[PDB]
Image (cartoon, rainbow, N blue to C red):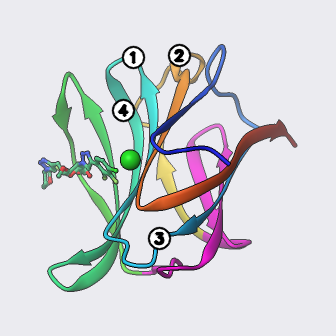
């Protein structure tokens, strides 16, 4: 286990067939979780479960370029629960990131940042206890 926030290094960036597994437990009174796939200051893929946005639960995904947030992709399917252990898996595919939570497909996010080999850090933050952060090639 590690104390958030934590940066998982991704040397030489990501590549198709790379499967990243984040294990943790959501804190009892959680407001938000965030994964940030970074290319320097740019955020290629921000995955942001929000427990209480306008008294609703929503997943927000976005890209940050030149310090500006772009078009949000939103999803009401919300597999997380306060207090509960989770597994987030991010499969890097040629054209998108594929996200599954607790072995169930959640969403796909098309690559806006094209230089996968430059996406060299994964930031993990928010209202979680982080157990594990690792990757393998499938
Ligand atoms: C509050 O900041 C968030 C941002 N955010 C969230 C965090 C974070 C920090 C720490 C922890 Cl522990 C953690 F969980 C975190 F989510 N940091 N930055 C991010 O979620 C962003 C996703 O679009 O939305 C907000 C920023 C934002 C969005 N937009 C518009 C909205 C209309 O559409 C076009 C633009 F997107 N303008 N600014
Ligand atoms: Cl944090």
The residues tagged by marks 2 and 1 sit, at their Cα atoms, a distance apart of 8 Å
The mark found on residue 27 in the picture is: 3
Residue located 25% across and 55% down the image: 72
Please tell me which residue lies in front, 29 or 72: 29
> In the image, which is nearer the foreground, mark 3 or mark 4?
3
Q: Are marks 2 and 3 in contact (CB under 8 Å)?
A: no
Residue at image mark 4: 43
Q: Earlier in the sequence, mark 1 or mark 3?
A: 3
Residue 60: image location, x then y, percent: 33, 61
Secondary structure at numbered mark 4: strand
Q: Which residues are magenta?
A: 77-105
Question: In the image, is the residue at mark 2 within 8 Å of ligand 1 by its beta carbon?
Answer: no
Of labels 3 and 4, earlier in sequence is: 3
Q: Is residue 32 magenta?
A: no
Q: Is residue 44 above or below residue 70?
A: above
Q: Residues within 10 Å of mark 2 (few under 14, many from 20)?
A: some
Residue beneath the point at 83% across and 38% down: 136
**Front one among 109 and 85:** 85
Q: Position of residue 122 (x, y in %)?
A: 53, 34
Q: Residue 86 appears at what percent x and percent y?
A: 64, 69
Q: Do the residues under discs 1 and 3 have CB atoms within 8 angstroms? A: no
Q: Up-down: is 51 above or below 74?
A: below
Residue 113 visible in image: yes
């Amino acid at each position: 286990p590690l104390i958030v926030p934590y940066n998982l290094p991704l040397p030489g960036g990501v590549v198709p067939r790379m499967l990243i597994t984040i294990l943790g437990t959501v804190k009892p009174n959680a407001n938000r979780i965030a994964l940030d796939f970074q290319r320097g200051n740019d955020v290629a893929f921000h995955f942001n479960p929000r427990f209480n946005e306008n008294n609703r639960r929503v997943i927000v995904c976005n890209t940050k370029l030149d310090n500006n947030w772009g078009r949000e992709e939103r999803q009401s399917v919300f597999p997380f629960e306060s207090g509960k252990p989770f597994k987030i898996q991010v499969l890097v595919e040629p054209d998108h990131f594929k996200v599954a939570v607790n072995d169930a497909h959640l969403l796909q996010y098309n690559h806006r940042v094209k230089k996968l080999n430059e996406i060299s850090k994964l930031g993990i933050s928010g209202d979680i206890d982080l157990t594990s952060a690792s990757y393998t090639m499938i």
